[PDB]
């Protein structure tokens, strides 16, 4: 997250760190949202590589013991069947990870609230992106979980020529684009939390930013629109 501030430890308890095994250690690669005690929602592109993955819940600082972490292997990876790695702009950038064990819920580990199917946010709706992604374009990952206020940019505006044009689909949510604050590499798969009727819900799964850079004016961060996938998510959980 570029232009973020450090999240409080208990603000975003559905946020997870998706990590892969690298030699004798583990490396953060993406975020995700805990949606059941044994299921995580993340981006399809986060799991294109043939890696060994684990999920960390109750994580705050990637580089030190928080006394709250639970570490769990990934048992099954269900990518949306229409996902195509060659074409992030097509959408379908979503995957569900079935965890090898069910995690224990507490102040630091909670299920993310998902929007009702089909829900669309008004332009400029209040949302926060969270993650440990790069804190600058071509920068380094955050140690501590970051948050940035990224108001939505509606589909009409976001798919206009000066923004993302036809690259953005109605299956996506855009947010930010102020040139200062944005998601960045390593935030992919994590939540966009938006305030609706007094409750934060996870409306987006971070998907892409501009090739030109993370915080680029009129290139808001693009997210898979969770509310377009409620049936798909329910269908997967019910059959696995
Ligand atoms: Ca830690």
Image (cartoon, helix red, strand yellow):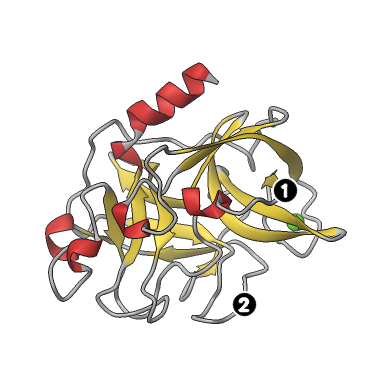
Q: Is residue 229 above or below residue 42?
A: above
Indicate the position of residue 25 as horizontal and vertical percent values: 83, 59
Q: Which residue does the numbered mark 2 point to in the structure image?
A: 140
* Residue toward you, 149 or 120: 120
Which percent across, then down, holds residue 75?
68, 33
State which quarter of the image contains the C terminus: top right
Across and down, in percent, residue 60 comes to: 67, 56
Q: Nearer the viewer, residue 33 or 24?
A: 24
Residue 159 at x, y percent in the picture: 17, 63
Crowding at dot 1, Cα within 10 Å, few <14 / some 14-19 / many 20+, comes out as few
Residue to which mark 1 is pinned: 52
Task: Name the residue at the top extreme.
Answer: 238
Q: Quadrant of residue 177?
A: bottom left
- Cα distance in 3D space between marks 2 and 1: 22 Å
Instruction: State which quadrant residue 38 falls in.
Output: top right
Q: Are marks 2 and 1 in contact (CB under 8 Å)?
A: no
Identify the residue shown where x is 76% and y is 65%.
63
The numbered mark at residue 153 is none
Instruction: Find numbered disc 1 in the image and state the secondary structure of the residue it sits on.
Output: loop
Q: Please, is residue 48 above or below residue 177 in the view?
A: above
**Relative to 182, is 27 on the left or the right?**
right
Looking at this view, is 215 or 49 the one in front?
A: 49
What crowding class fits label 2: few (fewer than 14 Cα within 10 Å), some (14-19), or many (20 or more)?
some
Give the residue displayed 17% in from the left and 67% down from the top.
165
Image vertical order of residue 233 relative to residue 156, above or below: above
Image quarter for ligand 1 equals bottom right
What residue appears at the point 35 percent right and 31 percent down from the top-left corner? 230
Instruction: Determine the residue positioned at 42% across, 75% down.
Output: 214
In this rendering, position of residue 114 left or right of residue 9:
left
């Amino acid at each position: 997250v570029v232009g973020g501030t450090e999240a409080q430890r208990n603000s975003w308890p559905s946020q997870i760190s998706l990590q892969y095994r690298s030699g004798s250690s583990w490396a953060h690669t993406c975020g995700g949202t805990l949606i059941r005690q044994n299921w995580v929602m993340t981006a399809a592109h986060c799991v294109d590589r043939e890696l060994t993955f684990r999920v960390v819940v109750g994580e705050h600082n990637l580089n030190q013991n928080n006394g709250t972490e639970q570490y769990v292997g990934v048992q099954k990876i269900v990518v949306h069947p229409y996902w195509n790695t060659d074409d992030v702009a097509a959408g379908y950038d979503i995957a569900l990870l079935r965890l090898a064990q069910s995690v224990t819920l507490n102040s630091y580990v909670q299920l993310g609230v998902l929007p009702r199917a089909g829900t669309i946010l008004a332009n400029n709706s209040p949302c926060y992106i969270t993650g440990w992604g790069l804190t600058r374009t071509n920068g380094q990952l955050a140690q501590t979980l970051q948050q940035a206020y990224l108001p939505t940019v509606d589909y009409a505006i976001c798919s206009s020529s000066s923004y993302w044009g036809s690259t953005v689909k109605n299956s996506m949510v855009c947010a930010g684009g102020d040139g200062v604050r944005s998601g960045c590499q390593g935030d992919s798969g994590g939540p966009l939390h938006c305030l609706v009727n007094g409750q934060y819900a996870v409306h987006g799964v971070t998907s892409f930013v501009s090739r030109l850079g993370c915080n680029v004016t009129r290139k808001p961060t693009v997210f898979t629109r969770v509310s377009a996938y409620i049936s798909w998510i329910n269908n997967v959980i019910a059959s696995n």
